[PDB]
Amino acid sequence: GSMQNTTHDNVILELTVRNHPGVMTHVCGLFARRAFNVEGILCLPIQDSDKSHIWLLVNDDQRLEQMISQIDKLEDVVKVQRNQSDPTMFNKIAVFFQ
Amino acid sequence: GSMQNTTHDNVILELTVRNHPGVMTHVCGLFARRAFNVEGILCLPIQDSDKSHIWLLVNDDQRLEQMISQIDKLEDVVKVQRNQSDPTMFNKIAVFFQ
């Protein structure tokens, strides 16, 4: 929660959304109104269909998971998973493409 | 309009924003109301300060650059550049971290 230089102070919040008009605005809106902004975003375009899997690097909060539960109910979110992991994962999946 | 047999259908729109409350929502809002959504997003956290440099992979449009000119006027956007390049650049800077 207190981003000093703590690498794993962030959390890897993945959600596979399909591209409905302004679905990127949904995730950005939740973390905006939360408390603190997103550190890093990885919207990896799923080439198979009209989809993209986004990893949100954001520091954990008291409201955080309640707001994940809210954004999860949006029908653009095809999938949503909460992973307590490092921003090195962000690099790994960006370079591997999966 | 949707990379069917090309890789260069998109455009690499970089903007170095500093983390004011809900600045990620600004870029997502512009491409939402534009016509077609963002293909791929790379919000690379600038570790030096409270900033992040985002590359927006989106296909070029008639309104596109007019809307870049709009979002550029927002004071969170510290820097903005329009580059007609490939999504391989997205990978390159994600893995190199710059």
Image: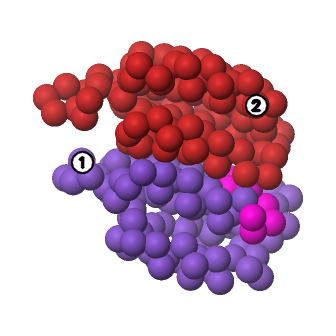
Chain colours: A purple, B red
Q: A69 or B67: which is nearer to us?
A: B67
Percent position of residue B28, x then y: 56, 45
Q: Is residue A45 left or right of residue B65?
A: left
**Circle 1: residue type:** Gln
Q: Is residue B4 left or right of residue A30?
A: left
Q: B60 or B33: which is nearer to us?
A: B33
Residue at the left extreme?
A: B5
Q: Residue at x 56, y 67 (%)?
A: A12
Q: Residue at x 78, y 45 (%)?
A: B19
Seen in the picture, residue B96 relative to A40 is either above or below; the reply is: above
- Secondary structure beneath dot 2 equals loop
Seen in the picture, residue A72 relative to B47 is either above or below; the reply is: below
Q: Chain of mark 2?
A: B
The 10 Å Cα crowd at callout 2, few under 14, some 14 to 19, many 20 or more, is few
The magenta span reads A33-39
Percent position of residue A27, x then y: 57, 61
Question: Is residue B64 at least partly visible in the picture?
Answer: yes
Q: Residue at x 16, y 33 (%)?
A: B4
Q: Main secondary structure of the magenta part?
A: loop
The 10 Å Cα crowd at callout 1, few under 14, some 14 to 19, many 20 or more, is few
Figure quadrant of residue A33 = bottom right
Q: Quadrant of the N terminus of chain A?
A: bottom right
**Circle 2: residue type:** Leu
Seen in the picture, residue B45 relative to A11 is either above or below; the reply is: above
Percent position of residue A82, x then y: 53, 77
The residue that mark 2 highlights is B74
- As drawn, the label of residue B79 is none
The residue that mark 1 highlights is A47
Q: Report the Cα–Cα distance between label 2 and label 1.
A: 32 Å
Pointers 2 and 1 in contact (C-beta within 8 Å): no
> Magenta segment: does it hold B58?
no
